[PDB]
Length: 190
Image 1 (spheres, one colour):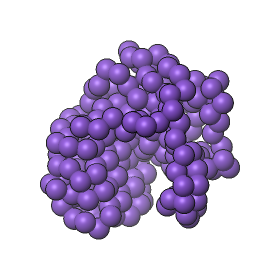
Image 2 (tube, rainbow, N blue to C red):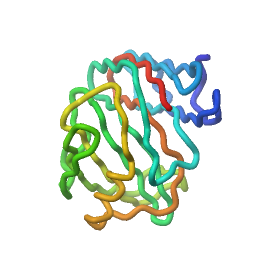
Image 3 (cartoon, rainbow, N blue to C red):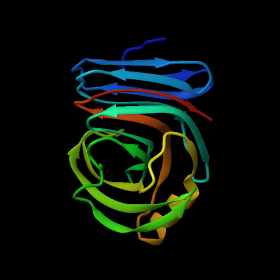
């Protein structure tokens, strides 16, 4: 159904839905690993389905539609602990490339497209363990798409060769993010 921000399990999948309380967002958990999100002049939000904990060799499949109107992105999103890292494998985005201002650390070919790799640091920002300073790792697909298969191992191995290590895996989901924009998406994970 439609639900307020929170986390839990639905039809076998882990889900996490968060928003800054601005409103204008509607997140709905559907059958299996499906979820829909409709947003209109929203605040900041992130929602998706996946696993808790994720793994370093998972092959993630997603399919559906993604129609952003503004700042937003579709990605495999998750965290690792010890070290604390937030990572993204961006498959599509709207008006803003989220890696802008980031330090390019390489490139990796995987699942039909080249990806550019970047690293950035977040200072005193919210995280799964409280306020902290941690790094964000990004893999941004050059050929955008709204369905496909993601071999996470290829990204995690490429990041490691570049000195970008990961700790113990926390959740790992396919999510839709929005930052003061509008759009709609319906994605099925598996």
